[PDB]
Length: 157
Length: 156
Length: 167
Length: 127
Image (cartoon, rainbow over all chains, first blue to last red; front, side, top):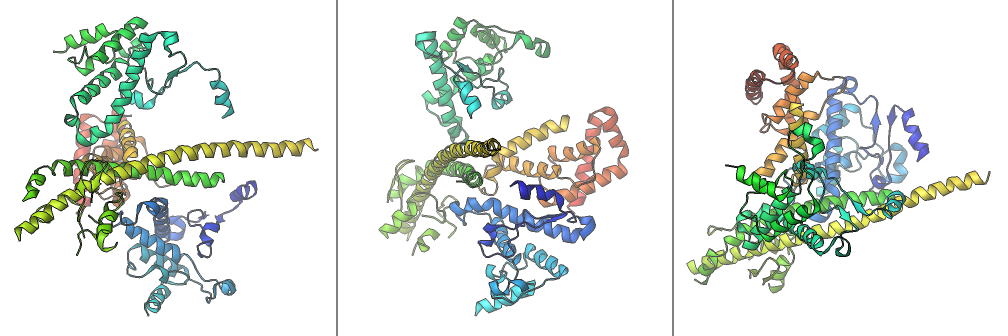
């Protein structure tokens, strides 16, 4: 639409919200493959921040490029490293969600604020395979990665 | 789209140049199955021109059907009829290529202008199986069917 | 409905067409080996699998019905590699059709050699049909897309014309 | 001109079979090869921002891919390989880079040089 389309060039960082994502219960409904920043640069954020960010987007883009396909052709017909990215991306998708302080009347969850290093670390860890044992839902609607671990214990019994 | 739609109302034939065809070394790079003509009609061009063109089209259509079986079963699993269609179709593909006079400088090869009756005759005889004994590369970059014979004799 | 919806649906079914055509090819090479491997193990015979997407292979034996093939327990590692002597069944007729101490192992191997010959034909056929259906759905959605393309352009122009004319 | 033609062809051949990848375990070695060579040239086309290359640095990198030296190298390691490999040829083989420029192409002599630089480097890389 001319209005938002013409607005993009005026910004240094863009957060793009999506109804498809919100429809899933993922809030904030940020499209991680359509949000950009001028400072997303290894010489500015350091190569660690950068490499994890690009890693997160790659696994989400790869999972997206498999979605419509396996959705009709079967999950079992996949490579043992494909279904590992599919499980990791599904967990990263969820770890991107977060209970907002402002959103307590919508979520029923206490709001969480996650410091930068903890965000980097958490996603860095899921990418390296460190939580393949943990179920998907443990990562849904939490703050830091330790809460994904705590929730995994609570879901067991 | 209104633009090509309107234009098509006026076209009596189409020449479709194919990047796939050129990559196979076939020049001119005319797609022999995609290119059409309104006057490809025995009431216009004659029954002999027609049936040879149809026979050529049919065989190039048939050759494609077997190409999935080519990559799977290999060539030596085909029937004696189907081995012969592959042979003839491959020969037809190459006999459709032609050196151009306008391209003599770039290639050194002498250009050819094939009369209609020699074109019909040539393709007529490959279908009949009069040149099954001939090697496939003899029909490539050649004018009339006589030069397909003179090229076949020249090769060791 | 929207160009955005058609573009997405077209993106997905174009892929599905390429997958099912490549799977047809995988199942075609596996069939030809299992077809020539059947003949010596047939006259010898007088004395399903894990992998789905192969028509009514798995369902047909289950309707008739310890089981061989992991699709039997759910309704291991069998079907993947051609059955050896070391490793209710489907009898191979053609590519298009099939029918549902030492003398014991003779029957096990024969039924197994018959099963994957029937499976790789049926998966080759199913994948052939899925690829052809996808191909039609593509041509149909392309025509829809271009009708919608033309209408959007025309609609947008008429909105402009009507605004200008009313000045 | 030389190395780019081969890359164009092999990428085009790659594009045809590209969908047989993630949904292929039981492929013939012919199409396994086209995929492998394809994913690897794709990695060589990746490039950082603000660091454009000299044409002879570019051909040296593409050479490694089109000649098949990176076929057994894991896809994820190619970008690291290139950076390192290029840092090397720039530091220690300025004359080889000087030659590819002067000669206008890769002569038999430059080809020989590269063969031994790449092979030994790659061996060192995977040590």
